[PDB]
Every structure is written in structure tokens, then in C-alpha cells.
Image: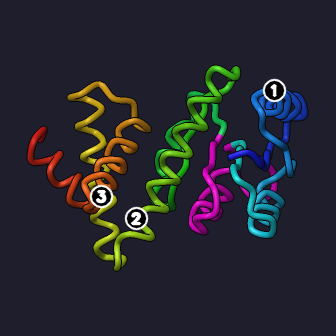
């Protein structure tokens, strides 16, 4: 991604987030102060990346994030106090998102973007490569299990684990499903 929508009601966090992003080569293409505007802007203008607070006026960050996630249009990072992180973990049934605990610096933000992007690539790949929804729902579960095994048994980060699956499937000229099934067979 390069083009970012930010949604944050606290002016200082918003300004600091914007500056962080600019310094690391992003362009800020939209700024919202509430969840309703965040949804409207994202759906109208299709940014590359959305970063939104979990708590926001009008439409809560989580509800907005779920809606945007459901449309499969962009990776989403949801900013949260440590104690509120479970709100995001619950919401991932809707699609690809990652939380980022506040307060945060760029060294925290960059890995959170990497994670949100990886998850978005996974949902995008599942939507495209798996024919039917009933298959897709179970293929998502399978790929998540295979990722887990690569993380725990081979020490990979979550994004590197999914990248491994995609690169294996591409190079071996097969599917994510088959690669994931073989990971389960081997490491499970």
C-alpha cells in the first residue's frame, strides 16, 4: 500500500499517525474523525490501507472495521488500548484486520501494517482461488491451521508463514488448499 485513510477522533494521535506514515513513504488521502465517515470514504474512494481507532463517535471503530472488512477492499489496522484488544479478535470473522496497541511508535506500526496486509492478501486469495463459499470457509480454517504450525514449529512470523504457503503453491503449481493440507500432514 501507499494511499492511506486514517480515522481517529483524538487530534494528537491522528497527527502523529499521519506524520509517521508520511515519513515511511505513505500518502494520506483521507482523514476521518468518526466511524460513519470512515466507512463512507473507504467505500467511495477505495484507499490502499485503512487505520482506525477501535473507539470512535457515531459508528464504533469495530463496527466500521467489520463493514469495511466485509467489502474486501483494503487491509485494516485497528488501534486499541491493550485491554480492548479482544474486541478486534472477535471481529475478524468479518474479514482481514489486525489490532495495534496504543500507545505506539513507528516500530510497532510497521509490523501491524505488515500483518494487516498479509491477512488481506489471504482473504483476497481465498475469494479468488476457491470456487464456492462453503469450501472457502473451511479453506480459511485450514490455511489458518497450517500458518499456525509454520509459526510454532518453524518459528515463522504470521506474515512469513502465509507468504510461504502462497509461494509454495505458486512455485509448485498447485493450490493453497493442497499446500496447507500437506503442512498439516507433516507438522500436525
Local crowd at mark 2 within 10 Å, few (<14), some, or many (≥20)? many
Count of all numbered marks drawn on residues in the image: 3
Between the C-alphas of marks 1 and 2, the distance is 33 Å
Q: Position of residue 173 (x, y in %)?
A: 27, 60
What residue is pinned by disc 1? 23
Q: Is residue 109 left or right of residue 161?
A: right
Q: Position of residue 100 (x, y in %)?
A: 60, 33
Q: Position of residue 7 (x, y in %)?
A: 79, 47
Residue at the bottom extreme of this rendering: 132
Secondary structure state at the residue bearing disc 2? helix
- Which of 36/187 is in front? 187
Q: Quadrant of residue 77?
A: top right
Do the residues bearing badges 3 and 1 touch, measured as CB atoms within 8 Å? no
Sequence-wise, the earlier of marks 1 and 2 is 1
Nearer to us of marks 2 and 3 is: 3
Above or below, 7 relative to 110? below
What residue is pinned by disc 3? 176
Between the C-alphas of marks 3 and 1, the distance is 35 Å
Amino acid at each position: 500500500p501507499r494511499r492511506v485513510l486514517i480515522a481517529e477522533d483524538e487530534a494528537l494521535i491522528r497527527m502523529d499517525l499521519a506524520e509517521m506514515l508520511r515519513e515511511e513513504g505513505y500518502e494520506i488521502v483521507g482523514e476521518a474523525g468518526d466511524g460513519q465517515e470512515a466507512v463512507e470514504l473507504a467505500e467511495l474512494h477505495k484507499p490502499d490501507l485503512v487505520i482506525m481507532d477501535v473507539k470512535m463517535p457515531r459508528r464504533d471503530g469495530i463496527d466500521a472495521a467489520s463493514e469495511i472488512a466485509s467489502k474486501r477492499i483494503a487491509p485494516i489496522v485497528v488501534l486499541t488500548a491493550f485491554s480492548q484488544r479482544d474486541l478486534v479478535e472477535r471481529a475478524r470473522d468479518a474479514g482481514a484486520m489486525a489490532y495495534l496497541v496504543k500507545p505506539f511508535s513507528i516500530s510497532d506500526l510497521i509490523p501491524a501494517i505488515e500483518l494487516a496486509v498479509s491477512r488481506f492478501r489471504e482473504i483476497t486469495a481465498l475469494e479468488g482461488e476457491v470456487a464456492t463459499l462453503s469450501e472457502r470457509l473451511e479453506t480459511r480454517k485450514l490455511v489458518e491451521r497450517a500458518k499456525g504450525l509454520l509459526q510454532t514449529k518453524h518459528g515463522m512470523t504470521e506474515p512469513d508463514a502465509f507468504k510461504w504457503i502462497q509461494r509454495a503453491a505458486m512455485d509448485r503449481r498447485t493450490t493453497m488448499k493442497r499446500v496447507a493440507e500437506v503442512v498439516l500432514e507433516t507438522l500436525g
